[PDB]
Length: 113
Image (cartoon, rainbow, N blue to C red; front, side, top):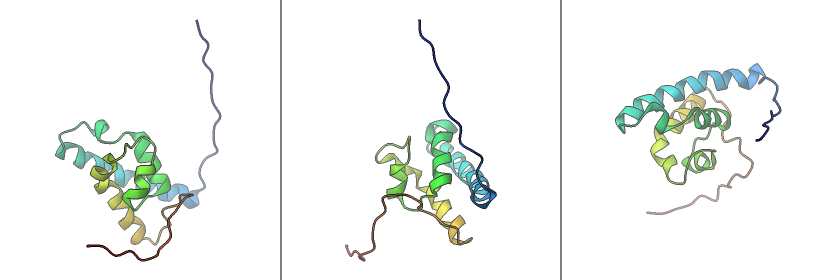
């Protein structure tokens, strides 16, 4: 047979950001749903809590950062646009910090099409 074990536990999040994540998370969940039916996929199939949670933490505004999220598979993120799309506005209207990733990209001002 085998014997499992338990892992560590992180301390609660400071209301400072915690709150923002709480209010945001709720917004995402709502979107995922209305979007789940559209694609004709179970509210869980579209995006699992694991994904939503991360998105609510990193608060990715660009699909690029979303892809980095855990659980999301390359490309899939795209379809999950309506999700992050809400984060960009939620923070844009509340001047809330976002894209709190480690490996970010500069702004050289691209030009295509």
